[PDB]
Amino acid sequence: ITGTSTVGVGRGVLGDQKNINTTYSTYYYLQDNTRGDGIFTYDAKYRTTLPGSLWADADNQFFASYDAPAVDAHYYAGVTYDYYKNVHNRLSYDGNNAAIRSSVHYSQGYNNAFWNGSEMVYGDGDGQTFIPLSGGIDVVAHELTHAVTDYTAGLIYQNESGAINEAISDIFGTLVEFYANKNPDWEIGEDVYTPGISGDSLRSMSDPAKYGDPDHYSKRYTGTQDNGGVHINSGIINKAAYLISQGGTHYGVSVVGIGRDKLGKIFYRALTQYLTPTSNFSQLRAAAVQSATDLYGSTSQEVASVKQAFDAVGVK
Ligand SMILES: [Ca+2]
Ligand SMILES: [Ca+2]
Ligand SMILES: [Ca+2]
Ligand SMILES: [Ca+2]
Ligand SMILES: [Zn+2]
C-alpha cells in the first residue's frame, strides 16, 4: 500500500515487547518499507486461502494475543533479511530485494510452517505440540532459507538432494538464531515446541540421534516416507556442519572446529556457487571442500576440518 513509514510496538508470541516497521494509510499495516522492496505480513484468519489480507491495525499497537504471531513473523523476517544482507551481501531471497510476504493464523490448530513457493505460511499450533510457529526465529529463518535455496542451487526436495535442502535450512536457521543472539543453540524449534516439556525440540544438529535421526551415512534412511527421508537424513549433514563449526570426535574421527562465521561462509558459497538441483551427499562434500579452498586456501585448517567433518559422518 502507498503511505508513510511508521513505527509500531507490540508483543511477540513469547511475551516480548518489540518495535515493528509499519505503513500508515488510514490503518497501520504490517508493511516494512525499510528493507528491500518491502516485508508484508498478512492474516489468513484461520483459513487456508493465501495470502489473506495485509495485516491492518487501527492504532499501531500490537499487544493483543491475536497480534502476537504476526508481530513475530514480521519482525523475524526483518532479522533474517538483515542476516543475509549484512553477512552474505544477499538482498532478500532472490538476491534482488524481492518482497518478503508471510501469512499467519493459517488454518486451525496447524502444527507447521512452510514456504509455499511464493511466501511464508505459519500455523498457530494446537497449543500442545506447538504454539504459534513464528515465535521461533530458527523456524522463520529455516523456512526463508528454502526460498534462498529455490533461487540458487534449486536442490530437489527428495532423497539426498532433499536432505541437503533441509540441512541447509537448519544450518542457516541456526546461524540466524546466533546472529540475533537470544538463547542460541543447535536444536530446531525449541522456543515454540511443546510448551509443557523443557529442553526438547524437533531436531538436534549437535546430536541428531536424540530424536531418532541418523548421525552417520551408514544409518541413512532409504525408504519412501517424508520424500525419501528429507527431514531424517538431514541429521547426517547437520552433524557434519555442527562438527565443522564446534569440533568434536564423532565415531573415532576428530574434527577441529573453525567456528560459526566460517561455517556460514563455506556453506553459503557451496549453496550459491557449486550445488545444483541433483547434488548428492558426496557432491556436497566436494562443494564444501572447494568452497573452503576458494575462501581460505587448499592447505588451510578450514579445508582440513571440512574433510574431517564429512569423514566423521561417513560421507566420502
Ligand atoms: Ca492495535
Ligand atoms: Ca534457542
Ligand atoms: Ca534453535
Ligand atoms: Ca518444549
Ligand atoms: Zn525445511
Image: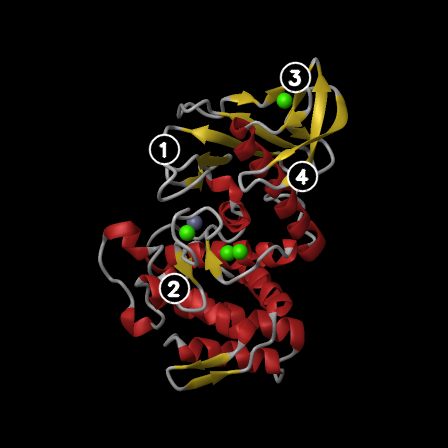
Distance in Å between CA atoms under marks 1 and 2 = 27 Å
Label 3 lies in ligand 1 vicinity (Cβ under 8 Å): yes
Left or right: 85 in relation to 230: right
- First along the sequence among labels 1 and 4: 4
Distance in Å between CA atoms under marks 3 and 2 = 45 Å
The residue under the point 53% across, 39% down is 13
Res 220 quadrant in image: bottom left
Crowd rating for badge 4 (residues with CA inside 10 Å; few <14, some 14–19, many 20+): some
Mark 1–mark 4 CB contact (< 8 Å):
no
- First along the sequence among labels 3 and 2: 3
Give the structural element (helix, strand or loop) at label 2.
Answer: helix
Mark 4 lies on residue? 18
Left or right: 285 in relation to 157: right
- First along the sequence among labels 3 and 1: 3
- First along the sequence among labels 4 and 3: 4
Mark 2 lies on residue? 235
Disc 2 residue type?
Answer: Gly
Disc 4 residue type?
Answer: Lys
Q: Nearer the viewer, mark 3 or mark 2?
A: 3
- First along the sequence among labels 2 and 4: 4
Give the structural element (helix, strand or loop) at label 1.
Answer: loop
Mark 2–mark 4 CB contact (< 8 Å):
no
Disc 1 residue type?
Answer: Gly
Question: What is the quadrant of the C terminus in the image?
Answer: bottom left
